Each structure stands twice: as structure tokens, then as C-alpha cells.
Amino acid sequence: MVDQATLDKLEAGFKKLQDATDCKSLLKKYLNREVFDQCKSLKTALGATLLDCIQSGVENLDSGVGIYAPDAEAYTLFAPIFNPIIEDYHEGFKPTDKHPPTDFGDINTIVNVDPSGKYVVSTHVRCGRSLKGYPFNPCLTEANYKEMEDKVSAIFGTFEGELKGKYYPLTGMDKATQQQLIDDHFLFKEGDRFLQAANACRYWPTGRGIYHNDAKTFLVWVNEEDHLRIISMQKGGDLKTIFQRLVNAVNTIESKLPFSRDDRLGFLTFCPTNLGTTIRASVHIALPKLAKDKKQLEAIAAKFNLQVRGGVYDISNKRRMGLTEYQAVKEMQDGILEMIKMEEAAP
Ligand SMILES: NC(=[NH2+])NCCC[C@H](N)C(=O)O
Ligand code: NA
Ligand code: NA
């Protein structure tokens, strides 16, 4: 049962969201009274309540989304509020829809997106994973964090080949090590107010750490937002080598530690934006001609299901759910190939 103290905070939060007439989060949009009354008295098997989902969007009213998952069960148990937010954010992933089974596909159909070297500065493929049996960061204990780091660092120690590298615990990290990792853009810090209000940064820095291979083309963040954030990257556009490295790595990890995955949602993540494939495939790319009209540059990316962010821009696949890991990477690749064709043919 939910304790009366949590029920009281929940009721105060619900009212606070209705009184913020100018607040525009997805949480506020879909947390109406009936959805709230459906959910407020539920509790997962690991002890997570609705407050462990919505507290950050109650405390930060400028949140774009405003909800996080405190454990894997919370996605199903609290479906009445998660499902409409997931649908909205992922642009048509309905409550009755289903994400495909995992498929990394035929890696040999993946190509270098810019053999010319003229346009793509670097290419990157990011994924995320939760480890089966562990709550998510809102509900992990100090002992969980410690035990998880022990198991994860043990696995990283077995990496050989191009994956062989070093684990750096944040606990007891010295300032020279930190500066070394900042220079590599490999360091993460305590979360901002959105994560703080979500109870994601408790017992910092216990259980948090960084791994990277000697080549500095592979990086893992442990307990930064998800249990594991796994990135493969390098200069140039060799998406084939990059993606295959990521897959080798994820498969190696999985062989020792099972992941949390849902038949409807795919891979379960702390934020609902990272569900499904979890894949974020991107290039840092300069398109001088196409970009001299940023509205049309954004329009062009938008036609290939791409998102432009921060001369050199980050262009990535917008879609995470409803498509396989292969299809997601292939969509970035085909979109980038086309935009380069356009840039090369533009006057
Ligand atoms: N982990 C993330 N990037 N989540 C996306 C949303 C972040 C923040 N809670 C917001 O809703 O604005
Ligand atoms: Na989306
Ligand atoms: Na193409």
C-alpha cells in the first residue's frame, strides 16, 4: 500500500500542476484527475510509487516531458499516464502499438556515410540499457549502486581487442584524472535539477563510473542517467565499423548481465524518450550550402526523419520506437547520404 505521506504529496503535486496554467509539460497534458486516481494508490513490487514517477515534473514545471520510470514494472503498472506521454513524444506510438524484437540486422549493408571526409567530422552511435533485476536510479539503494558497479566493472575488465580499456570510478576520482577525462569529453557530473528532483543522483558518486577503450572510440557511462550508456564513435563516417563495435560490446555485456526489456516498449530506460531501440545515431557534419537557409536545412532533415541540433551540426535519427535497431541506423545513414548528395549538387 502507498503511505499516506506519499498520497498527500501526490495530491499536492496534482493540484500544483493544475494551478500552473502556463506549464506545458506532457505530464500536465495527460495527468488528468481520472488518470491520477487510477494510478496514485499503486506500488510496484520493488516499492516504487506514482510519486517516484512524476515528482520531477511536479518540481520543475518547465519540464518538456516531466515523468521518469523508477523501475521496470512502473511502465506497465502506471501505463495510464506513461502510455499517452509515450504516444505524444514518439509521434504516434499508440497504447495498442508494439515495438519490434531486437534486430541489429546485416551489418555488411551498412556503409561509410562520407568517404570524402569533406562533410562529416565524426560519427556516433549511442544506446542505453537497464540491467534486469535492478530498480532504476530513482529507487536504487547505496548497496545496489555499489553491487552493480562491482559487477559492471568486472565485465569491463574482460574486454579484449579493440574494446580493451580502463574503468574509472567516480568515487575517489582525483582532479588530474577528471581533467584528463574532460579533455576527452568523457566525464559526467552530478545531474541537474531535473535529475535531482527525480531522486536520480542519490549517494553520488557511489556506483557511478566511466569506461573507455584505449583507442578512445568506445565509451560507457555507468549510472549517469541509465544503468549503462554505451557509445561507439570516431572521426570520419565509418558507420559500419562504429555500429559493429557497439553491437560486439552490447552482446559481450549481455552474455554476463541480462538487460531489462518489455515486449511492448522494447528496452526499458529511465526516461521515456529513450525507449524501444534506445538508438541515437548521429554525425557531426558541416553542410554550408544547405545550412545557409536553416529553415530548409531543418526542413530537409525533417523529410528524412532526422533531427538537427548543436558551422558543424549534430544530425541524428529522431525515431526510437516502432522500428528495429537496424532500421534506425539505416535511416540516419540514408538521410545523411542524401543530404550530402544535395550539398554536393547545390550551387
Ligand atoms: N533524460 C532525458 N533527456 N529526458 C528528457 C526530458 C528531460 C526533462 N525531465 C524534461 O522533461 O524536460
Ligand atoms: Na520522437
Ligand atoms: Na539513400
Image (cartoon, helix red, strand yellow):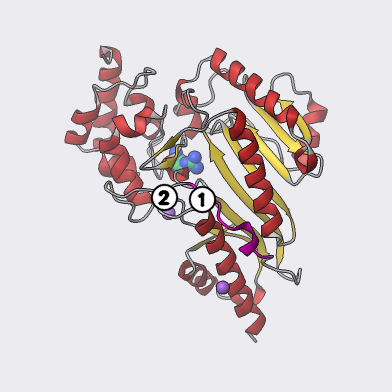
Is 108 covered by the magenta stretch?
yes
Which residue is located at x 35 percent, y 29 percent? 74
Residue in front for this viewpoint, 25 or 208:
208
Q: Which residues are magenta?
A: 102-111
**Residue 148, quarter of picture:** top right
Q: Picture coordinates of residue 25 (x, y %)?
A: 35, 44
Mark 1 and mark 2 in contact (Cβ < 8 Å)? yes
Residue 80: which disc?
A: none
- Circle 2 sits in a helix, a strand or a loop, which is it? loop
Magenta: main secondary structure equals: loop
What amino acid does circle 2 point to? Pro
Along the line of sight, which residue is nearer the eye, 60 or 262? 262
Where 93 sits versus 109, above or below? Answer: above
Going by the numbered disc 1, the residue's amino acid type is Asp
240 in relation to 146, above or below: below
Label 2: which residue?
100
Residue 103, numbered circle: 1
Residue in view at x 29 percent, y 13 percent: 5
- Residue at 71 percent across and 43 percent down: it is 218
Can residue 298 be seen from the camera position used here?
yes
